[PDB]
Amino acid sequence: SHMCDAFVGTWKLVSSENFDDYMKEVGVGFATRKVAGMAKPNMIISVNGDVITIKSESTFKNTEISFILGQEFDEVTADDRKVKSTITLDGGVLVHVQKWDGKSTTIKRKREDDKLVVECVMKGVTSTRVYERA
Ligand SMILES: O=C1C(O)=C(O)CN1Cc1ccc(Cl)cc1
Image (cartoon, rainbow, N blue to C red):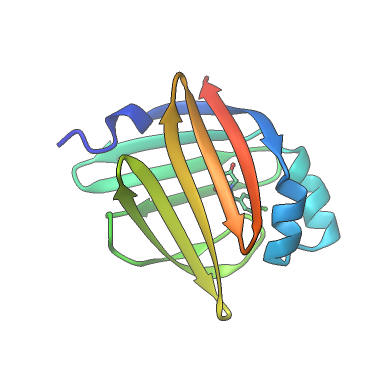
């Protein structure tokens, strides 16, 4: 049903801003921040029926999530948090909320021009990560 069509594909990270500070706010430790911050992941997004799959492949970690919009799931993040996640579409933006230990962070993924822009927010700290088609 052409849900998420403009997101589907293989995307490569081309810029990052404020990611170390976002990771600090989330609680990521020093060594993981350094290695994770170096990574240039590819994000691979696909849809099969109602199921969306987002894979992230990098030299740091490979991650994979599959989900149905609005339906909570378990996620182990790249930094090894065990979180409860819900992903919805809000006005054409994929909004990914992660909950763990009474904390919450939100990752928004949006298409803007030929890029896919990822905004990661923890309390007052935002990181913006820009991906281009691979
Ligand atoms: O899901 C994404 C995505 O498509 C990014 O660019 C950043 N991110 C969150 C994130 C948090 C912590 C670590 Cl260690 C690694 C990634």
